[PDB]
Length: 429
Length: 120
Ligand SMILES: O=C(NCc1ncccc1F)c1coc(CCNCCc2nc3ccccc3[nH]2)n1
Image (cartoon, rainbow over all chains, first blue to last red; front, side):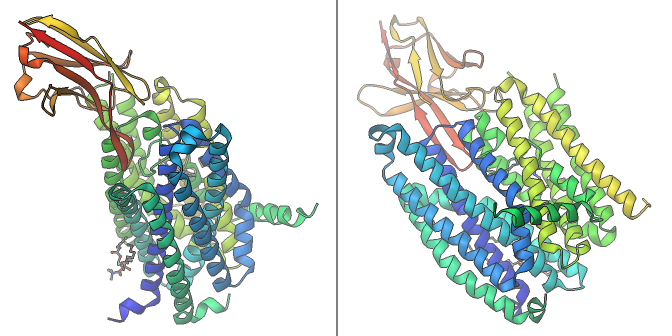
């Protein structure tokens, strides 16, 4: 059983541990937001705006840093920064949960605001490090480990997505059970300790991956960062894979989704916790099914064909959702149609996400890989920022319908862009 | 996200009553609203419920038929209409919300409660 020590499985294990830590810490921050502050749209929206704006500004910088440095150095530095930021965030969360009563009742009104500012800043740093490690590990390391074998690359990307979704659905359950059977302070302490141990393990895991793969070793003072940012965006605009990236970014403008504990429109609206949990589980299983569908489609059709088919599926499911919205309290038929439309949209969208990921991994030269992927993340977070702005501007319930249309419209728009990419690449159906 | 109750009092056996539960911090059209009875000398018991997504009622067998639970989203309230009250229904009624929160972190939120007395 040499599979347990191969580069591919060690990469899988490292990604699994990193994603588990990330999701546990995300759930801890969500619990911090819910317990201290009420179910407020403004606070979660401000957190999302801060994270999205920071990544939008610094995507090119992070990509350039990944591109200009050795692979092991950037991977380990990003790992250490992410885990240390998560450890500090966990310690602060344990401290606030320990003094929750005093903060809510006895202490002045500025201490809670200071705690929120500190938590969102540490979360922004952790998310920046997570974006850096995602860029480097996924793009560079998975492409190099796969090499010239595209089937292996597609299987590795699909397995990464499956691990990500399973962790997204399991880590909230584990942290919730731990917190309830103990206390939120115990939960935050466990999260901090687990992140420390996982950092220690993942350092050695990345070092061992770097050994078994010998191909990884080959490869105003703000004028320079601004020049790198401009050069990165100009290079991104001149890539053949640009409309596909634009479509993938536009697919982030949607409100229709159940994959996020906080910053989700359904939770902000006031939907019951049990229904939200059921919908998140259904979205996770359907996302796994979508990754399987992508892996199957890529072999039969091409890759651009796989993207087109996935976009067609997602548009059909969102058409079902629109029919639900326009269908004449509210009848349970409309709600069931909307939920089915969103879930089947997820199954049709994960395949397109994997297709665009494979296109970026294949058609971006090794010299521009980090910068182009950083700019792609910047575009994704820019359209996520637009989504958060839209959610802020329309908080009243009797506008939800409108949002749906907007969201669906953008999806269509995104896929239209990808369709143009197809016409620029194949010229055949 | 507390909710209050009103409409309790003392009525003759076989009369009619309407208990109104007003919620503030959440929608009532998407949360499973419930009613509970707490009788003197014994633990609280289930009375009625209403679904979260649709509109379905789940009255308990002991009080099924003579009770009605109806939600109103415009006023964000839940009404328990009690008809043909019996002397053993004298208790304290608690409005309840089950599974309110985020995805995997939800709780049960109770109300102050209203005293209902039945005499013959
Ligand atoms: O379709 C969708 N997304 C496309 C997609 N997803 C994943 C892979 C590929 C792909 F193309 C979709 C559906 O619902 C939603 C929810 C709204 N999005 C914002 C999520 C969020 N949470 C945040 C927390 C902190 C900071 C920033 C945050 N941004 N997004």
